[PDB]
Image: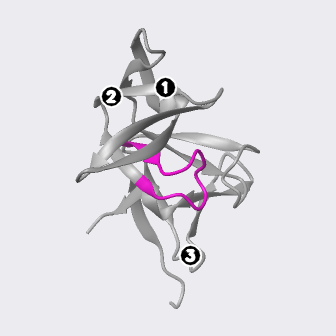
Amino acid sequence: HMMENINIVIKDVGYFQDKPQFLNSKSVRQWKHGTKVKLTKHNSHWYTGVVKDGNKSVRGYIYHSMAKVTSKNSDGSVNATINAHAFCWDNKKLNGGDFINLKRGFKGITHPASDGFYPLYFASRKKTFYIPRYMFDIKG
């Protein structure tokens, strides 16, 4: 049994990445569901904001479906609540194509991936989706 499975759970967070992309980005923050933040609209699909790591200001980007806007500030910023969810994609670009919104706490099975693209086989679909490491925990 050289082949292995991994039980995974999708994190209870929204992803505030160092770039407005899911591939080859680092999390500046993984904000718990319900966290209240200030953001600015960056484009049709992304918000941006700034946080402090020590005295250093760091910019991040969060996908529109992970941020519920509750009010609009005069300076053009917005006040929002984080809506935690993840994604898996039918290709390793992690950008459009066929993708699925995975609910916070979604329980899945995957396999060791040397390239960091963890495969999810959905019976109902006839296809492999891919989830990056940073969107899930391994029970243990």
Mark 2 sits on what residue?
37
Q: CA distance from mark 1 to mark 2?
A: 10 Å
Residue 113's disc is: 3
Location of the C terminus (image quadrant)? bottom left
Q: Residue at x 69, y 61 (%)?
A: 92
Give residue 95's position: percent from left, percent from top.
69, 48
| Furthest-bottom residue in this view | 2
Q: Residue at x 24, y 51 (%)?
A: 55
Q: Between tags 1 and 2, which lies in front?
A: 1
Q: Nearer the viewer, residue 136 or 45?
A: 45
Which three-letter amino acid code belongs to the residue tagged 2?
A: Val
Task: Decide if residue 39 is in sight here.
Answer: yes
Q: CA distance from mark 3 to mark 2?
A: 34 Å
Question: Which structural element holds mark 3?
Answer: loop
Mark 1 sits on what residue?
40
Question: Which structural element holds mark 1?
Answer: strand
Question: Which structural element holds mark 2?
Answer: strand
Magenta stretch contains residue 136: no
| Furthest-left residue in this view | 54
Quick check: marks 3 and 2 in contact, CB under 8 Å?
no
Q: Between tags 3 and 1, which lies in front?
A: 1
